[PDB]
Amino acid sequence: TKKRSNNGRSKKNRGHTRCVRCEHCSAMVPNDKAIKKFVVRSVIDAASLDDLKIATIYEEYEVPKSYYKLNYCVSCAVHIKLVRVRSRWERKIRKEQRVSA
Amino acid sequence: LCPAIQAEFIRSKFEENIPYRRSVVSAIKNIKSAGGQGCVIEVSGKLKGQRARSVKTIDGKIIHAGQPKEEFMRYATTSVLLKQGIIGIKVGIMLPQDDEGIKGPVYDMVDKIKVLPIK
Amino acid sequence: EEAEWFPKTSLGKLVKAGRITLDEIFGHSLCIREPEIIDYFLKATLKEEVLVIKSVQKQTKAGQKTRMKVVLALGDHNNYIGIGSGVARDVVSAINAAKVVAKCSMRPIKKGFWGNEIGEAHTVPVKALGKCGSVKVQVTPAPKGTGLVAGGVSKTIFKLAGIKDIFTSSKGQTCTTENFARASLYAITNSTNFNMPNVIEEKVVELNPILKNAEFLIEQEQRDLR
Amino acid sequence: NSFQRVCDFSLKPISSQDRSSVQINMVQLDERGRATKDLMIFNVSGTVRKNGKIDSMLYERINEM
Amino acid sequence: MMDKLANLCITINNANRAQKRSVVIRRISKVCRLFLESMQKHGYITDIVYIDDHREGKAVVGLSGRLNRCGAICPRYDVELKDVERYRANLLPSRGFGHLIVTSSKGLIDHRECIQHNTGGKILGYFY
Amino acid sequence: GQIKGKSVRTASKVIVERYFNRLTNDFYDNRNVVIDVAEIRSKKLRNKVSGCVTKLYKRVKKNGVPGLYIKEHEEEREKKESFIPKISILDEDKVEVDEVTMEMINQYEINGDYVLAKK
Amino acid sequence: AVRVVPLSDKVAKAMVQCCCHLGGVTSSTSLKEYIFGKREEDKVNIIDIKKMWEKLNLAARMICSIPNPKDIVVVSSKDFGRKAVIKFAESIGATAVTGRFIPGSFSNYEIKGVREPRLVLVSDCFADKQVVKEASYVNAPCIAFCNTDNDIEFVDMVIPMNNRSQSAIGAGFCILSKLVNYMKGNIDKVEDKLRDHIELYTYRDSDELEQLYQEQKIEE
RNA sequence: UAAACGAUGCCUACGCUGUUGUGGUUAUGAGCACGGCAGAAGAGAAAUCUAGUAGGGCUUUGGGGAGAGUACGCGCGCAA
Ligand SMILES: [Zn+2]
């Protein structure tokens, strides 16, 4: 029986879409189906900022950040616990997740 | 209110070759009609074939735990010999409360609370 | 040994006091929520027939738990019919339960003539259809003196409803006795409510009898209190 | 008799089984806007009630009167 | 394109179910007029106005509380006077009321008038 | 875990509604009253009932417990209501209000000292 | 036209101060007929006064039609709107329900203390949804006060008014009480007792009542 | 030749509400074409709804599992 109204993907009014590759296992997954995750990570760890304050030559310094978008296939997303199995009424709830660091 | 009588009514009916169901249903009616506030009956053995089972029936109120079981509850056990083996019978009855102390205890259970009516 | 009836509901007060008739009840579409109301008027006349007994099962860790399900009809051979189902550990208990449902769902059934209006009305007025689950039943009027052309279960229902001639057709899985019984009762019911050409002129209007008798009931309020 | 109840808003008979049918009663205004012993009476089916359509329909008919 | 006599029927059937009292019907032909005029003679509909819009045509009609159902038959079968009662028993709910309409050399007539005039014709539609 | 259990809270709630005026802020008064009125067969229970009742009586006399109607405090709340507010919208006869309301005032010709909202 | 007990100037003034006419921002196809324009500054919809008086009169009329007034049941399951019901019902002889309406309490005989209704009254019927639903089982009409954001299936008489402010709730109940009494001849003019009653009904915090107590006692 | 799938033929009808898009036009109130979403009422064995109402027109197509989309003949293809 049909488990989801949208077939588990975001394609509508189209024939075909570009593929992308999974970060964890390099499998091909369609772009409109892949699980997506955003990361904004400081170059320097929080446990070093108190040393940075005496190491730097400049009057003040702003740490550089690094930015990423990651893609996962279903198997990897479930195994890494980005997503979890949910009850028949919970399946319908849609909410934006946090940006990781 | 005597489980030792009722169990022998049951044992009789097995030898009379009457179904356990009909026999037990009659026993429970007699126990309840005589004023017992509940009872338990179990039959166990080679009762309907080569595979043995036990069938247990409950009606009304029965107490299992603590000192209130020693004063309100009465039990009997018997067995009947048949061509295929021995069939065992257990009967338990919970006595009614009785203010003159003949049929059961004078004082009702220790955990029951009753609040008096206002004038 | 018997128990006297104290009416739980407002309409119940009126029937016991003797201020109302069974046609007035049906005519105003009043709820029935006390079986005693039907007993009061029809106890001396009601017949019943058991349509089906069957055993149902629930699987558990210990094994199958099981119960008896019974379905029956109450009716008077003149005007009234109702259908009821009950489930219990015992076939007797199940019958007691089913009877309550039946009484709380009695209906009056209208009748008519195949041709001209000579003699007494004897068939359903108009060709009609009733559906329940996968089962569909259609009833058609019939000439006087044809009898009940009807299948096993539905035949009993027409007889209790006081119908003398009918033609019937059926579609679907009629082995399911509950569906076949409910569908046929809907078919006759639908025929009684058909919008006949005369209906608009036959119309009458009245105030609801519970509003009409408010004064008496207010006395009964004070009588119970005092 | 048992077969003489007809719905005012939808012009069809009401069956004995319909739990959602209701009868609405209202008094008539007196001279100088007070009350009287005479009553308006309406019989209304369940079908209109499940839809929600009764609100507007009644307002229409009090105007018709 | 849809058949105009079919369109007429579905338009009034749905509006009746939705408990409306009046409708506008959007494409009209000569036999559609005669069909509506038949329903007026037997008191199934009350008021008729025709709009002369120069684009086909359209009608506005008032429904009575007496109308349960109507319908067109397609195709329009030819029938002898011997055949009409077969169709009468198939379409109508009761022997006492309702109308089956037939086209003839004497206009639209009902299944009773067929006996009076002694004529078959072609089957057109029904209402009750 | 020191939770009171169902019969103890039930008897507590009933006694405060049935005999409210007889009770006080004092454990020993309350223990005397439950010793007097109740059927309770062990001091172990009535120590717990009078404990909960004197725990309620503070909260109840301190402007009420929701879910616990006492006629004495329905009267106290009627006294607090009979201590009527002397605040007034009633003297605010001069007013300013929006244009849409001023046109409703016009279309129904409503007399009074209204103004357009100066805003 | 509909025969309605005449408007009087102080009454008109009263309702406007009580902010009866301030609707919400949303609207519904059922309620379009009662709106007369929208605030350019605020997007708030403004209610038509003449129509408000009409349906208020219509409600009053049918309240008079039912003998033994105890059979009228008034419900309002919220603080911020509680005390109004408690006084209002006494002014007409009706019964009332105050807390949570126990579901099944009209349907089921075993739940004690609420009478079989012959007419149900509700304020702010987003709450008390159960009451509107349950009355439908027992052939009772329903009268509700309502606002443009919300819409109901089984309500027969929808009186339009603000229901989200303690100023407003008082005004509706206070006025309707008087009309019902007037229609029966229990009072001779409606302007008789404005600021007394409309204040009595109006909700107040414990914190206010402390201040008012101290004031009153100083004055005494 | 494909799980060439929204597993839902093509024209043409009659049909409840709220919300959100894309492109033009606008008495600025709205419309027309192409969509998404959330209820309702009906429907259906249910799950659910491209599935509501209906003798409108025309084509394809199924008739308990298996053997079998296999044998023989024929048509296309370099073969597969
Ligand atoms: Zn992967």
Image (spheres, coloured by chain):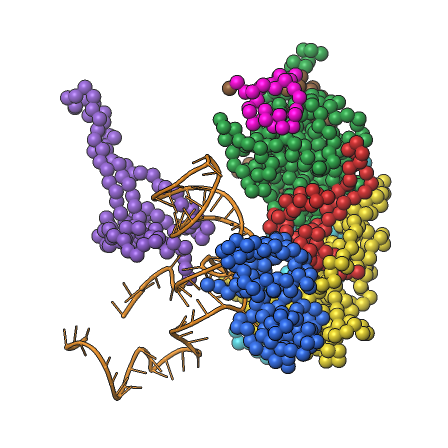
| Magenta region, residue range | F91-118
Q: In which quarter of the image is residue B32?
A: bottom right
Q: Find residue F41 and report its horizontal and vertical position in percent.
A: 69, 40
Chain C shown in which color? Answer: yellow
Q: The orange chain is which one?
A: H
Residue F109 lies in the magenta stretch: yes
Q: Which hue is chain F drawn in?
A: brown
Determine whether E32 is above or below H77 in the image. above
Residue F78 seen in render: no
Chain letter matching colour purple: A
Q: Which of D18 and A58 is in front in this view?
A: D18
Q: In this view, does C178 lie to the left or right of H17?
A: right
Whether B58 is drawn above or below F104: the answer is below
> Quick check: C78 left or right of F85?
right
Q: Which chain is cyan?
A: B
Chain G rendering hue: green
Please tell me which residue is depicted at 73% across the width and 78% down the height of the picture. C143
